[PDB]
Structure formats: structure tokens, C-alpha cells
Length: 247
Length: 248
Ligand code: HEM
Ligand code: HEM
Image 1 (cartoon, rainbow over the protein chains, first blue to last red):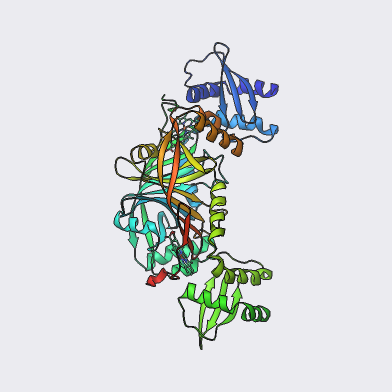
Image 2 (image 1 turned 180 degrees about the horizontal axis):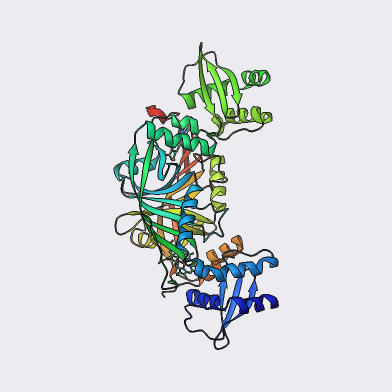
């Protein structure tokens, strides 16, 4: 760690000040120097013989990668503000799924947490659902009280407490069978490969393609890296820094 | 194909009738016989000139596996009824997750679809969430209007249209810091390995452990394999067969 300490103190002092402020609410730190790194995080020293420990978002399994993980953490402070990059991540994130989770309000007054197959044509997204499923009644009766969530697989996520997610308050509407329907479905068949029952449900008339018109969105890709979305506008949510601990 | 047809006609005639009834709502079929199998499904012939095609829930890439895939589908008709086996699968399914999806009702009136880390002390399950998140207001103000979903990862599922899932109408209640909190949190650290920020959020006072009391549940593990659950009782939902296409 001796070499790492030298490296950080020589090229990432301003980043460390950024980390101290963002994660520790330490605003006027002096004598900022890198103290250590271990498989789970780093320790930054400052001021009156003090330190702030900041954990990585995963365990770094090989000591050979401690340096890069530390650099990534230091660079995350400014990267948080690369809105163009976040916008591109959001687009690519959505393209990596063939299904989404939903919250709907059923006519029985109870919320419903479910999931449905996701399809798309251009920038238009849709879900394909059956009248037999509990979420159908809510999509039909409360079409504008719906939230759609793109949630990263637990097995692909950094940890159980940081699964990347993209959520949108959504207005829904039914799409009748026809040209629009076939374009979305053919696209789904091509992308997925079309096996597994997909061909069967296309012919089941109790299934409906429902367009998703997204309104307010919230994207979370890392600790202290949450964003609000609306149309083509995206804004970082934490200019004030760590809000936890009743900050 | 000749050997597979011969095998199915000699050993699975009753299963094929079961599949015709279940998936095709064909009840008085005669002259039932196995017709073919391909990478995506099987075809059963019946009557003078009719057939029913039933797709596998995944593509069988190697023809060496067609017979087993076919036998699996045939045997699924009766296996669907094994409630003791389903009970076992449900318990094991929940133990395979360290997080769940949630639907909550925000005080403003809109529903919220989110997710939270999942913890437990034996049979008691809990979630751990922060006051900074939108689902907190619904968990605090509409604590008995919540649905928890255990959803299989898309990358592990048979397909996009068949991700296994277990959903429960749930009543929630807050757990104060103390011995119960520590038991659940310590168990979570030991299970997950405790890296990635878990240790940091334990100390954040804006986070609360919330116990989940599951009520009605619905488990879906395959096509035509959906079950209703309430406490210690489980029941198969499809006695009437394929409900799709407005079969009523
Ligand atoms: C022929 C092949 C079948 C296919 C491809 C198929 C497909 C599907 C799909 C994709 C859904 C999800 C709908 C949604 O979430 O909106 C579904 C739900 C359902 N299916 Fe089927 N199904 C088939 C046969 C059956 C049969 C034979 C039964 C009954 C014995 C059945 C009973 C159900 C029930 C009860 C649900 C609702 C499950 C839930 O709680 O989400 N299905 N089916
Ligand atoms: C010290 C490291 C941090 C850790 C371990 C951490 C952890 C978490 C966790 C686990 C959640 C999800 C809570 C829930 O869904 O109930 C969360 C949410 C959130 N955090 Fe942090 N956080 C950290 C720092 C920060 C900082 C520095 C900011 C602000 C600049 C921040 C802003 C937020 C916001 C806005 C949310 C809500 C996200 C959402 O919509 O789901 N966090 N944080």
C-alpha cells in the first residue's frame, strides 16, 4: 500500500477532498492524505489526526486491483456530473432488458407488485400482459397510476444493497392488434430468439400490448449517484451531499 | 423420431391426454398419439386429423435431449399437483434472495414500484430501507397495503415471459434498534459476506428494519403452474385448465 499511498497523495488529493465532503460531510479538511486500502474500502486521513473510511461498492477480491478500485472511487466524484454519460447509461440500461417490474393499483384497493415482458419499437416501450394476471385489472381500471421499474439482476449487481434501477411514473394505454402490434412483437421475437412460449402467447387473445408513456423518472447507479429524469432533462439529486443520518 | 414416437405412445398416452386437456382444452380426444418433437416443442395428434402443439419453456439445443424434454413435459401434468414439493420450492426460492421488489402506496395516492435489501431471522423476513427513499412514505403511512415480490433474475430464468416469481400481500411494522435488529443484521452480514456498503448503512439512522408478515401469496414456476398460498395452505390454481383465450 506504500506505493498506492504515494500515488494517491500525488495525483488524487483534490478527489480525496471531494470524497471527504460528499461522503463524510467534511467541508474544510486540511492535511488530506491517503492512509490505506483493503478489500472493502479506503481510509483517508485529514485534520486533527482524523480519518474517514469509505467502503467500495463491492469486495475487491484481488489485492492487485486495490489501486484501480481506489482510483475509480476517487474519480466517481466528478463522473457523477457527466450527465451526457448518465443519459447514455440510461438508454443502454433499458436496452438490456426484455422485462420490467410493475406497481399497479388493483380495483380491490390493494397495490400489486408484478413483472411483465417488455417490448419496443423505436423509442416506444410496451408491456405484454394477460387478463388472467392480477396486474391486468389495475392496468385497465387505473391506467395512469402505474410505476415501471427496470431493475438490475441481483446476480449481476455490485451487491444486494446496490442493484441499479430506473423507475418511471407511467401512463399506460392499450394497443389494438395490427401493424404497431406486429412491429413490436416481431422485434421482440428477433431480439429474444422467440423460443420458450413467446410464439404461443402472441396468439392468446387474452393478452394485450400496452404502451408505456414515461413521466417522472429516478435512476440510481451508485451510492450518491441518483438522478431525476423528465423528458430529455436529467439532473443529479445530491448537490447537498450525503443526506443520510439526517444530514 | 421413430423411437421417440414409439416411446411416447407406449409410455405416456395418459400424459398426452392430460396435456391435451390442460394446454389445449381438448377433453374427448380419441386416437391420441405423439407426432413430433423439435427444438421448440412437441406436437400431439388426435382424432382423425387434428394436432395440438405445446412449446417447451426453453429451446432444447441438442437433439440428444429431445426425449427427456418431452418426458419432462409429459410428467409435468402430474408433478404440478405435488403441493409438498411446491411448499419446499417456495421456501428454497425465498432463501435464494438477499433483496425483493416492492409495491407501496404513497400518501399522495400513487403507487410506487421499488426494491429493498431482504433480511431474516429464521422464518421471519424483514426489509431495510431509508427515509430518503420514496417507498418509505408508503411503508410508514400505508403499512398494511404492500406487496412483496421475489422475482427470479432475468439472466437465470427460462425466458423473459417465464421468470419465476412469488408475490405476497404483506403487512409491515417497524423494528426498533436492539437485539432483534442485531440478530437479523448480523445474519445478513454473515450470509452476504457483508461487503459493499452494508456495514456503512447499518450505522445510518435514517434506515429502518421493517418486518414483513406475509398474507396471501401467489407463486408461478411454470406455464400452468401457478399456486395460491395463505399461511400453511397452498392450492394449485389451474384445475380448470388453460384459462387463456377466454376459455371460460
Ligand atoms: C399454453 C402455454 C401457456 C403459455 C405460453 C402461458 C403463458 C403465460 C404468461 C406469459 C403469463 C403471464 C401473464 C402476465 O403476467 O400478464 C401467464 C399467466 C398465467 N397462466 Fe399461463 N400460459 C400457458 C398455459 C397456461 C395453463 C394451461 C394454465 C392453467 C392451468 C395457465 C394459467 C395461468 C395463470 C393462472 C396465470 C396468471 C399467473 C400469475 O399470477 O401471474 N397458463 N401464462
Ligand atoms: C456513504 C455512502 C452511502 C451509502 C452506503 C448509501 C446507501 C444507500 C442505499 C442502500 C439506498 C437505498 C435506500 C432505499 O431504497 O430505501 C440509498 C438511497 C439514496 N441515497 Fe445513498 N448512500 C450513500 C451516500 C449517499 C450520498 C453521498 C448521497 C447524496 C449525494 C446519497 C443519496 C441517496 C438518495 C437520493 C437515495 C434515494 C435513491 C432512490 O431513489 O432509491 N446517498 N443510499
